[PDB]
Length: 42
Length: 41
Ligand SMILES: *[C@@H]1O[C@H](CO)[C@@H](O[C@@H]2O[C@H](CO)[C@@H](O[C@@H]3O[C@H](CO)[C@@H](O)[C@H](O)[C@@H]3O)[C@H](O)[C@H]2NC(C)=O)[C@H](O)[C@H]1NC(C)=O
Ligand SMILES: *[C@@H]1O[C@H](CO)[C@@H](O)[C@H](O)[C@H]1NC(C)=O
Ligand SMILES: *[C@@H]1O[C@H](CO)[C@@H](O)[C@H](O)[C@H]1NC(C)=O
Image (cartoon, rainbow over all chains, first blue to last red; front, side, top):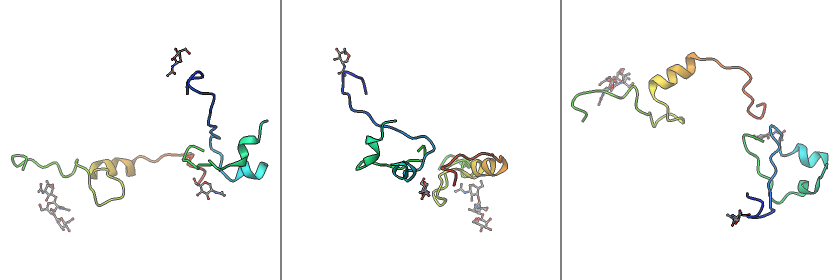
């Protein structure tokens, strides 16, 4: 959202399956999970 | 009761998983695409 609204962000890995990012584990702290959501876009 | 006019072939068909009409299904079948790009399924 707007930067002044909040510094919280979400990351989309386009065309990437939610198993490949855990498999790999560039910042990787987001790879921990607890919010992973597989979409048709990535 | 549209005064005797028929719109069944262009109105949605609830039966199918997709709510496309008969003619819309016809068009989608006729046109063939490539490189789906859907999680490479
Ligand atoms: C409005 O839409 C179309 C034409 O305007 C009609 O479609 C077909 O109409 C007849 C009777 O009206 C029926 O045909 C039968 O359909 C069954 C189911 O597919 C099929 O097994 C039979 O062999 C026969 O073909 C049916 O209602 C309908 N479907 C087909 C394939 O013809 C429709 O009936 C019209 N009805 C209304 C309320 O507007
Ligand atoms: C963000 O834009 C301006 C300046 O940052 C600020 O006045 C405004 O209140 C902020 N908008 C929202 C929805 O927080
Ligand atoms: C790839 O993503 C789809 C969901 O879009 C999933 O069904 C499938 O299991 C995944 N394939 C893997 C993890 O190998």
